[PDB]
Image (cartoon, rainbow, N blue to C red; front, side, top):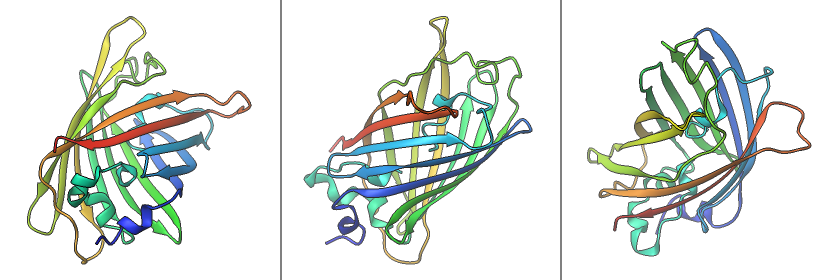
Length: 226
């Protein structure tokens, strides 16, 4: 008994498209890969189509499909993400980079045929031209962490909150505080959950054969706290 549940039974193709502007720095990213919600597994490869990425890849990871999360059988009734499919949902965010600029994001996640699409437009402002971000002082990696989920309303969506800790080259750490809201695109029914969280793990890599600026990402996500 689940609208979107059936959709995530096998390996689903993913298409990611982002349009960003950060301090007047305009760029575009395209991504392709697949997801297997059974294992909470994701494999994506991103390419900066406009040349060299103005910001650091690691800062984009979170922006670049939580419907691929693995919900244990006992927690299935809490899967809002899959429940909004195939119609989709809106994922909006504000990411405050401590002592630096912020990112404003608005994405739409939905199926286009049998392809899971993530269409995003990002807006970045107040960045320090010499900060860790514009300054590119961030390490090419990513730490594990949790994602906190809570419902919003009685038919509406969810609010999610969490912090990312980006490692700097000097051993220090750059904080990225995420504020996120999700709203279903249709007028159909959706699963509203009790509080829980998602335990995420990500590995960033590079493709030796790839001459363009890009990032290879492997992510594993599993619901818990219930």
